[PDB]
Amino acid sequence: MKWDEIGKNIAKEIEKEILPYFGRKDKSYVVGTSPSGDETEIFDKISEDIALKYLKSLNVNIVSEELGVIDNSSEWTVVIDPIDGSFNFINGIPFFAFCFGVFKNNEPYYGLTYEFLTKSFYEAYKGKGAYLNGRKIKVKDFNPNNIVISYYPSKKIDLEKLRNKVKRVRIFGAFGLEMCYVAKGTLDAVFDVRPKVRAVDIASSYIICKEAGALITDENGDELKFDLNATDRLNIIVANSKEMLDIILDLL
Amino acid sequence: MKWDEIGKNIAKEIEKEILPYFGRKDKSYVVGTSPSGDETEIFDKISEDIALKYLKSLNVNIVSEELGVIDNSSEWTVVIDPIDGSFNFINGIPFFAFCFGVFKNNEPYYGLTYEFLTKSFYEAYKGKGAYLNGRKIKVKDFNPNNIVISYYPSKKIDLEKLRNKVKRVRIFGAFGLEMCYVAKGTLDAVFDVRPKVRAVDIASSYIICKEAGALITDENGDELKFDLNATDRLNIIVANSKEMLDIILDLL
Ligand SMILES: O[C@H]1[C@H](O)[C@@H](O)[C@H](O)[C@@H](O)[C@H]1O
Ligand SMILES: O[C@H]1[C@H](O)[C@@H](O)[C@H](O)[C@@H](O)[C@H]1O
Ligand SMILES: [Mn+2]
Ligand SMILES: [Mn+2]
Ligand SMILES: [Mn+2]
Ligand SMILES: [Mn+2]
Ligand SMILES: [Mn+2]
Ligand SMILES: [Mn+2]
C-alpha cells in the first residue's frame, strides 16, 4: 500500500462521510477548540478521525490541525489538514480540500491535495513531478500584465499598490488548495503576510509546488523554512517566479 | 412549456457538452470579439449556440453576451450569459454558472441561475420567491461583527476602510453567481463599481435576488434600473440589508 494509495483512500472515504454537510450550516455543532485557536466543527473532527483510523495502525508521527501532534519517534511523519477551509465548506462555498503530507526526517516525500468538488487529486513525490489526475502540471510562465493573484495582506500592506499591478484578483479562502491553483498555472501567486497559515495547511501543497516550479519564500523574500506542527502561524509567499515574487515582496 | 422547464433544459444540454471542457485551457481559444468588447471563446460560443437552438423557435426576443441581441418585437425577452465566469471555467476555478433571465415587457418575470459544479438551480418567479433546488431561500440577518463581502472596486474606493470594517473578503470572479450567494446567505454583499458588469451578468439573478429579499441598487444607492442589451456596462451593489448598503455606500 503506497503513500498515495493511503492518502487517496482516506480522502475518498472522507469524501462520502462528509459531503452531506456541504452548506448544511444547521447540521454542524462545534466539538472544541484546537491548538491554533480555531474551533473544531464536528465536520472537521469526523474527517480527521477517518484519517486517524488508517495511520493509527502504522508506526508514524502525526500532525493534524484539529488534534495536534502525535510523536511516535519515526523518521516518517504525516501532516493532514482534515478539511482545508472549514468556513467555505459549512457556508456552501465550493472551495475545500483534503491535505495529506508525508515527511521522512523532516524532508518532503509525497504531498497529496484532494479538491472534493472537482475530484481533482493534486499530488507529487519529492523529485518526480507534480501531477493532476495523472496529467503533468507545472507553474505558469509569468506575464507582467496578466497577473492573477490571490492575497491575504496586512494592515501595513499597501493595497492600491498591489491592485494596480495585478490583472485579476481572486481569494478563495483556502490557502492550501489555492497553492495548487498556483501548482497548475491558474493563479500567478498567493501570499498571506498576516500570519495565520499553520504548518498543517501548507504541508502537502508545499511539496507539490516545489515539484511544479513554484518558489515558496517567506516574508523577507527568503527560502521559506518551517516546523512540523499544528501550532505556530507563519508568513508564506508561494509564487510563480522571481519577477512575480519580486513584485510581491516590495509591495509588502 | 413552462419557462423554468425551458431554462433547466437548456442548462442540462450546456453542461452535457462543455463540462468535459472544464479547465482544459489548451483545447480552447478566442473565436470572436463580443459587442461589449470582450473576446468570445469556443466554449462560450458553443454554450450560447445551444441556447439559441431552443430560444429561437419560441420567437421570443433574445439578448446574450456573445451574439448581442435578436429583436423579434415580442413582449417577452430572454437574457442569456452562456457561461458566467468564463475565465475560471476555462481555468479550473470551479466558479461559473448559466444565467437565464426571462423578461415580460422589459419587466422581470423569471430567473434561472445554474451552478454547474454543484447541481444547484437558483430559480425565482416574480412574486413567487427565491428557491435553491427546492429549499426556500432568503438573504442573511446582518451582523457587523461577521460581514463576508466580495467586491470589485476602482480608484476612489478606500480599501483601508473596507477590509478593516469587514470580517472576511471573498472575491470569486463570477458576479452573476455571486449574486446568488448574496441571496442564499453566504455573503453579506457583492458590489461592482468598476463598470464591467452588464445586464446579461445580473438579469436572471436580479430577479432571484430581489424575491430572496436583497436590496439591489446603483452608484448612489438609487435602486438598480437597467436596460436589456448586451452592452452598456453598469455599476451595481447587491446588498444584504440597509446597513451593508450603508457601509458599501460609506466607503464609496
Ligand atoms: O479569507 C480569510 C479566512 O476565511 C480566515 O478564516 C479569516 O480569519 C480571514 O479574516 C479571511 O480574510
Ligand atoms: O475577477 C475579475 C475578472 O475575472 C476579469 O476577467 C478581470 O479582468 C478582473 O480584473 C478581475 O478582477
Ligand atoms: Mn480551522
Ligand atoms: Mn481544517
Ligand atoms: Mn486548513
Ligand atoms: Mn465575458
Ligand atoms: Mn459569460
Ligand atoms: Mn458573466
Image (spheres, coloured by chain):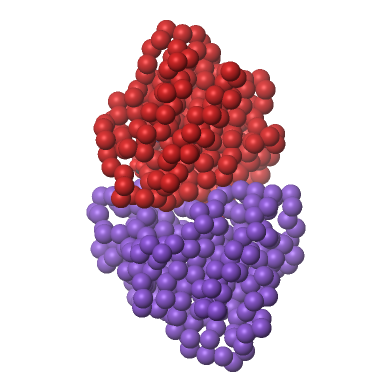
Chain colours: A purple, B red
As drawn, B226 above or below B215: above
Q: How many marks?
A: 0
> What is the quadrant of the N terminus of chain B in the image?
top right
A94 versus B176 height, above or below: below
Q: Nearer the viewer, residue B20 or A219?
A: B20
Left of A203 or right of it: where is B68?
Answer: left
Give the residue displayed 50% in from the left and 44% down from the top: B150
| Left or right: A42 in relation to A179 | right
Left or right of A68 on screen, residue A179? left
Residue A24: percent from left, percent from top: 69, 49
Kindly indicate the quadrant of the structure image that contains residue B83.
Answer: top left
* Residue B96 x, y percent position in the rendering: 47, 41
Task: Tell which residue pokes out farthest to the bottom in this image.
Answer: A73
Foreground of the two, B76 or B58 = B58
Q: Point out residue A81 in the picture as x, y percentages from the top left corner.
A: 57, 69
Report whether residue B206 is seen: no
> Measured along the vertical axis of the image, is residue B171 above or below residue B42?
below
The residue drawn where x is 52% and y is 20% is B102
Q: Between residue A164 and residue A123, name the one nearer to us.
A: A123
Relative to A113, is B210 above or below? Answer: above
Query: What residue appears at the point 64 percent right and 30 percent down from the top-left corner?
Result: B130
- Please say whether residue A1 is visible from this viewpoint: yes
Q: Residue at x 68, y 53 (%)?
A: A21
Residue A7 point in image, percent of width and height: 55, 72
